[PDB]
Image (cartoon, rainbow, N blue to C red; front, side, top):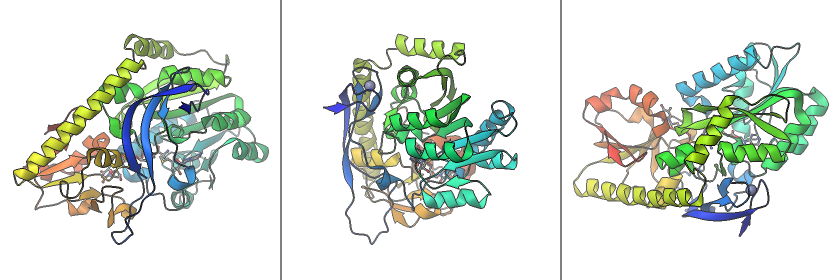
Length: 405
Ligand SMILES: Cc1cn([C@H]2C[C@H](O)[C@@H](COP(=O)(O)OP(=O)(O)O[C@@H]3C[C@](C)(N)C(=O)[C@@H](C)O3)O2)c(=O)[nH]c1=O
Ligand SMILES: Nc1ncnc2c1ncn2[C@@H]1O[C@H](CSCC[C@H](N)C(=O)O)[C@@H](O)[C@H]1O
Ligand SMILES: [Zn+2]
């Protein structure tokens, strides 16, 4: 039995996705076929309702000099983060000498807008290659993990932060209590800790199990974040649902009683209770649906091959590691994966070892079918790939059901 990382309660497993590789490691084709693996399974705390993985991957195996994800690769996301930055500039950063800290700034997708406004800021980016990309834009970055001690160090030299922000980053820190202690040492008394991550309600509704992989330790809900904040002296004071990344919620935490929660918080809590979101039975039914999507997806991919149809994948997502390894999908069923990230191209995907090629290579003559791993980017991608569909090529999606369009 494993102990909850928020509260120490007991975690009950409901989904076992078996042995899995590191999702963001892309090997050269000549590399030894050895990879770190771990058991990926998900459970729910008995006491605080936090849904979480049962085995942690050590941080330094995932996040380091060669981490390959570049935030600024999506036009939708560049606009999404510039707007959030302007919203903070108009609201929480209007003081004399305001200060914003971002946890997980990556290539500077959000902080560039802050820097261009002349506002004091600091990004934490322990993956040094993407940290350098942010520093080239004139952003101030420290190549360290955010945790209690590094937060203390920033408080000592820079003073309190008006906003601490994290997007797609808090989800992967199992040492969330250390981060909370850091936020407590660093945040201004009237500041906010704002984070946005994949939402449990969307995952259950869409059967989007590919959101579950080594860099998604927590599947947060308003119910579990409310408990986590409270147990640490914060309070959930606003929630906003976001369409990005398959469905997210942005959570705003303030010191307890310092601000009054928006009506939005109670509304979302009540909908999660009515829908029995976090009940073990609902979560087990989700797990049953995961197996049905596996079985349908592999039946389709095998019938396509029996029918002489060509199949590739589009987007070398981290998420796709779960799909290929749980369903047993490799290059005999999906020949190549197309992707815009230079450091993933001319490499093999983890576990399944499908070759990754540049997206500029997806061109006439097109394959019959493209398995859309980057399904969270469907509008942006399909807008760029109208010629493929006009030519008769079709997309295979597995969210929220296996279907072709
Ligand atoms: C828009 C676009 C993307 N692409 C390619 C680029 C990417 O490799 C991938 C998309 O990856 P995308 O769904 O954004 O994240 P991933 O699941 O990897 O997940 C990563 C890792 C991480 C931090 N743990 C996380 O949660 C999210 C934020 O990021 O697809 C195109 O080829 N053409 C395009 O037009
Ligand atoms: N403890 C921690 N502190 C700060 N950054 C962290 C961290 N653990 C991991 N990271 C960083 O978290 C980032 C997640 S990538 C996504 C980042 C970006 N905010 C976006 O939303 O697109 C990686 O760049 C990784 O190095
Ligand atoms: Zn718990």
